[PDB]
Length: 13
Length: 163
Image (cartoon, rainbow over all chains, first blue to last red; front, side, top):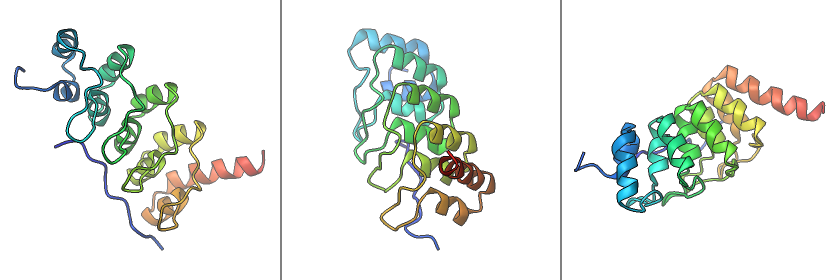
């Protein structure tokens, strides 16, 4: 894969 | 190796072929389909020696991916401290957001990378800047239960207030 960044939370809480 | 791109060579840490492919063609900052430079691939796979080599040979660490991914953020996300230090010493922006609303500090915190968090804060990363959702780096560290990280961040904030 192209390296990818992790998905961060859309909200915390 | 004939099949491998410059990006892949950098990712694998194949210094010899990588150095050759650079003499054959001016491709040191050639971006792939996603805007990723060889440097970003190297940063993402923790290839310290390749990062050093590319930066010495004129690779531009400020170039960003299609979604404004940075070499800095890629390195931070995986906790590659030595690479983070090298890029910071190039004077890249430490507080910029990508399209997925991530910053180097949020990626360091997300991955529980304490030494990376410390280094970013010492280089001017601001732990109070917020995502579009309203949470900041301290919030995220609390949310995720990363206590050593929460403490580095709080300690930094406290020392700012105590001068």
